[PDB]
Image (cartoon, rainbow, N blue to C red):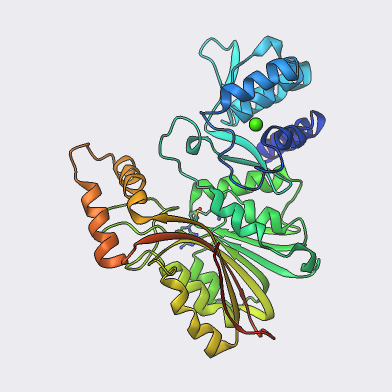
Amino acid sequence: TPPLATTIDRLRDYLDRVGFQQIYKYIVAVNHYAVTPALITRNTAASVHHFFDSRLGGRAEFALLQCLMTGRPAEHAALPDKDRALADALVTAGLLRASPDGREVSGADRQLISAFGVDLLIDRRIHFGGEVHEVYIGPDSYWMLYYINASGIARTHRAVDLCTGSGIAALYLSLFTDHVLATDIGDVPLALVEINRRLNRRDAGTMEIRRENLNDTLDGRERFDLLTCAPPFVAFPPGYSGTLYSQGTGVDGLGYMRDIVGRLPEVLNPGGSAYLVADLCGDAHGPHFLGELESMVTGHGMRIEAFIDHVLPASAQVGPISDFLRHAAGLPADTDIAADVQAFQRETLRADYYYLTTIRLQTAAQNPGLRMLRR
Ligand SMILES: Nc1ncnc2c1ncn2[C@@H]1O[C@H](CSCC[C@H](N)C(=O)O)[C@@H](O)[C@H]1O
Ligand SMILES: [Ca+2]
């Protein structure tokens, strides 16, 4: 809407005025900035507040910035005059809260971060409070984008970010090409990527946002030079309900990965490349999914490179998966979810380990083959 659009314009003006992106980059430092979005969290916010208070002297020009970054309250009367009208607009938009007596502003459900040179509003509940969030972002998103060869992107390359969520992959691609498609089906992420597109001075002139199922985009007539996708891929036991952003399709959670890879020879232009990321089950030698990709090498002459950037024994995921299932469905604490997850890992997934894997796939490769990089 026009009032929201103007509010976001003024918010980006504020971020530019006070150098938000540089401050965020300084706080997390260059050895963490691209590792994970979980840097400013409930466990580090006190440290962030101390930095602003003592190293930046508590200057009022950073007050509204901290409401957005950590949720820290700022007294309404202490905001500079230009920041105070913007703060009122953000409260009206539901992007910040006012205290009940109207005397301060503080965090709502959106946290402001930066990643890959882009300013991004994300679901605050993933790093603060702990309540089940409605939009995902994780280190996996970052590791996808890290492996993209940005110098090979032309302005006229057609790129698509499927299952865009907050929009981070689409906004990254929009740094380099003027033709980006970003898709999702959730009302909440779709609203958020609209905001984040405007927040980075973009509009439908160079980035289309589309409400569309993954398989519809992939079956379509559109052809792309570059594709990214971090799709729902978590595998939950039969009977359990996850969330739209987490639960993968198929018996092992990887149905969306299968869907994408199978259509790449038809959806990419020859020589185009796709970047995917998923947490893949496997044995001691590696993720089971890579065995399915040999059909792509032989049948389509692709080059497929898998970058294994984190390994965990399956037993280390039982708690996190069970906790997530318990909270997402509001289950009580006497349910034996842990045994259900274990049995599912053992019997259906055959998962001794989980491999957090980025995969680059190229069509019409001059050096076809499958390559697995492990440390
Ligand atoms: N069939 C489908 N088609 C398109 N998007 C889907 C989909 N099923 C789930 N989604 C969306 O897929 C996203 C996965 S979370 C991924 C968010 C983002 N790509 C990131 O890496 O941070 C969620 O936003 C969810 O709404
Ligand atoms: Ca730090």
Tally the marks.
0
Q: Residue at x 44, y 78 (%)?
A: 291
Residue nearer the viewer, 268 or 215: 268
Image quarter where the C terminus lies is bottom right
Residue nearer the viewer, 152 or 244: 152
Residue 206 visible (yes or no): yes
The image quadrant that residue 249 belongs to is bottom left
Which percent across, then down, holds residue 337?
23, 47
Which percent across, then down, holds residue 62?
73, 22
Q: Up-down: is 209 above or below 68?
A: below
Which percent across, then down, holds residue 103?
60, 10
Residue 71 visible (yes or no): no
Which percent across, then down, holds residue 70?
59, 27
Q: Up-down: is 201 above or below 13?
A: below
Which residue is the extreme one toward the front? Answer: 375
Q: Quadrant of ligand 2?
A: top right
Which residue is the extreme one toward the bottom? Answer: 299
Q: Residue at x 39, y 56 (%)?
A: 247
| 285 on left or right of 163 | left
Image quarter where the N terminus lies is top right
The image quadrant that residue 361 belongs to is bottom right
| 238 on left or right of 218 | left
Q: Residue at x 32, y 42 (%)?
A: 323
Q: Up-down: is 97 above or below 172?
A: above
